[PDB]
Image (cartoon, coloured by chain):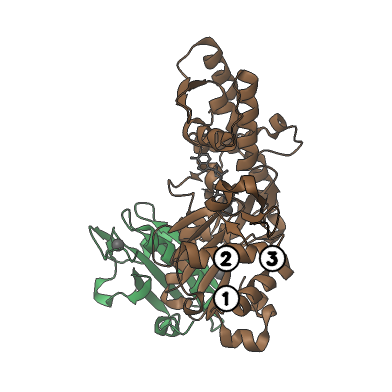
Amino acid sequence: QALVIDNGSGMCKAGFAGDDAPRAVFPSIVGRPRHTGVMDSYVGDEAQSKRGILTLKYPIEHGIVTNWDDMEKIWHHTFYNELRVAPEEHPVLLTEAALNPKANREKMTQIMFETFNTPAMYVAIQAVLSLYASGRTTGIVMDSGDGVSHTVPIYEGYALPHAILRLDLAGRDLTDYMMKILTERGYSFTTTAAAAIVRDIKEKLAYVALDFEAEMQTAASSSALEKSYELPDGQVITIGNERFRCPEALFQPSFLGMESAGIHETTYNSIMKCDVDIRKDLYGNVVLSGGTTMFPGIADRMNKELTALAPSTMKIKIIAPPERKYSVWIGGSILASLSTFQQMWISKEEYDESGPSIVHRKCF
Amino acid sequence: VEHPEFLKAGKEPGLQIWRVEKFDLVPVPTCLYGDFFTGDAYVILKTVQLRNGNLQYDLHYWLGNECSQDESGAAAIFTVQLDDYLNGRAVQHREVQGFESATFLGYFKSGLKYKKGGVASGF
Ligand SMILES: Nc1ncnc2c1ncn2[C@@H]1O[C@H](COP(=O)(O)OP(=O)(O)O)[C@@H](O)[C@H]1O
Ligand SMILES: [Ca+2]
Ligand SMILES: [Ca+2]
Ligand SMILES: [Mg+2]
């Protein structure tokens, strides 16, 4: 029974190979007692609940591990609190970013074998996992999550590292931006549940405009785009153009005072860094992945932006599976379930002789 | 991979066809070749004998309109793995029901046929 762990910038997704969905999804947050031994750690929602008396760390805010004691706490919580397994009994598949530093892959491997005593483990690139989950071996993955977005071109099963672009905003930025534009509209979010309220407004009411200026006009001229939202305390507020302006920052990072290219352009640019002969296949298999690609309208608008950018006879297909919040996780579950996968794992035995660098020869 | 079927694959000129059944690669009876369950995904290897003595490989993964996510995902993956196994020598093709390349359709002398149903998801 293999386990599948997707270490997300914001959210950790964890589960059992063979299941169609993660059994556990929790925030990648570690909480430590501000003032020690006057009255230890907490992970996930419990750390959030108790944040008033905790110092909270985010050990992977941009997809890469910045703190190994806190990452270890996250894994301990994943194993013991969330999945309730003994880790020494399960092969474990873990995901990483495409450009995960070489020392990080080795550290992750070391921790699994030495700290959690896993009998087997494997590290997989997230974008390749989403591609697989979509039933493809070639395509470009546009993954936008919580603290990190990337475009990863993949040809016949393997990412093209030289063509990977790290797009500069994600979910957090969009939540921050939804808060600011709601404040400006007249509203005030002052409780400790402010982030959460605005995140939820983002998740339930935001959409991506097919033609943004025409939407701005429709909205300035009528009331047919507006939506009511009921706050925790029963107060009802109205969400107008904020619904589409917020995710628009994905296409116009300038809204956030950012010089960076938007998601359609980052996508283009990646395709352009690839052998000319494979680009047609990239354009015809643009796969959307991650929470921040969940906005309604996002596929149409990507189709539109990339049509505009590519020669007019280019066949553009955008693939936005409804389950794309978990595409990475689901790719991992399918991979780790395959009859041919027992040969792929780094075993304990292999670890004990090669040590942690075995990862660069086993996992790519 | 020590999968018995990888050991059988690309050994001589020919067509081989496997069905994804529950995260496994299961060979299709040669008498049923060309009859595709639209609720299934399959891996097809076409080995052609070249003038040099070496064999050419084209690997097609065929996706039924109703195959489950685990089956289409496994077909794509098995394809990558079989290609790695054949020293990267296979050209990989994604074949979708109703949109198969002429090359793929060409493999089937009495024309390929669709039939409803298949093996259940492995999830
Ligand atoms: N329906 C939705 N619409 C817009 N954003 C969403 C939706 N559901 C989740 N999100 C956002 O997705 C981000 C997390 O997605 P995820 O892919 O789990 O990130 P990561 O893997 O980087 O941790 C969060 O910012 C969350 O607010
Ligand atoms: Ca089936
Ligand atoms: Ca190949
Ligand atoms: Mg992610």
Residue topped by disc 1: A116
Query: Separation of disc 3 and disc 1 at Cα?
Result: 14 Å
Q: Amino acid at mark 3?
A: Trp
Disc 1 within 8 angstroms of ligand 1 (CB): no
Quadrant showing the N terminus of chain A: bottom left
SS class of the residue under badge 2? helix
* Residue at 27% over, 64% down: B120
Q: Which one is in front, A85 or A130? A: A85
Q: Amino acid at mark 1?
A: Phe
Do the residues at discs 3 and 2 belong to one chain?
yes
For the residue carrying disc 1, how many other residues have a C-alpha within 10 Å: few (<14), some (14-19), or many (20+)?
A: some
User: Which callout, 3 or 1, points at the residue further toward the start of the chain?
Assistant: 3
Q: Amino acid at mark 2?
A: Trp
User: Which callout, 1 or 2, points at the residue further toward the start of the chain?
Assistant: 2
Residue topped by disc 3: A68
Residue topped by disc 2: A75
The hue used for chain A is brown
Is there a contact, CB below 8 Å, between mark 1 and mark 2?
A: yes
Task: Report ligand 2 position as a quadrant.
Answer: bottom left
Specify the subunit that label 2 lies on. Answer: A
SS class of the residue under badge 1? loop
The hue used for chain B is green
For the residue carrying disc 3, how many other residues have a C-alpha within 10 Å: few (<14), some (14-19), or many (20+)?
A: some
User: Which callout, 3 or 2, points at the residue further toward the start of the chain?
Assistant: 3
Disc 2 within 8 angstroms of ligand 1 (CB): no
* Residue at 26% over, 66% down: B119
**Against A29, is A177 above or below?**
above
Query: Separation of disc 1 and disc 2 at Cα?
Result: 9 Å
Residue A79 percent location from the top left of the image: 51, 67
